[PDB]
Length: 8
Length: 8
Image 1 (cartoon, each protein chain N blue to C red):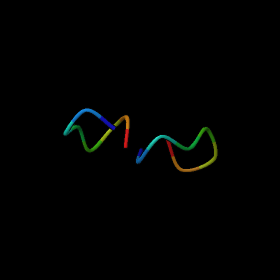
Image 2: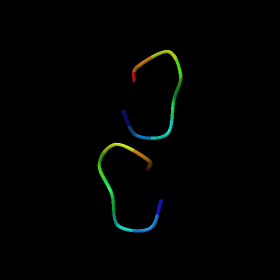
Image 3: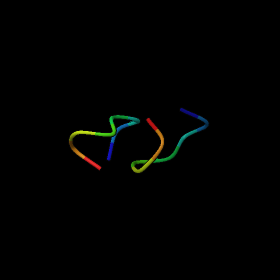
Image 4: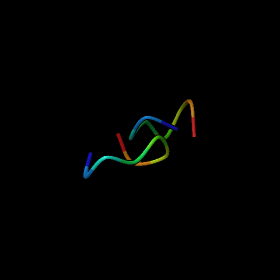
């Protein structure tokens, strides 16, 4: 989420 | 981005 591939 | 939670 939030444009982060870590967070999704 | 673009007003989206997912994209940031």
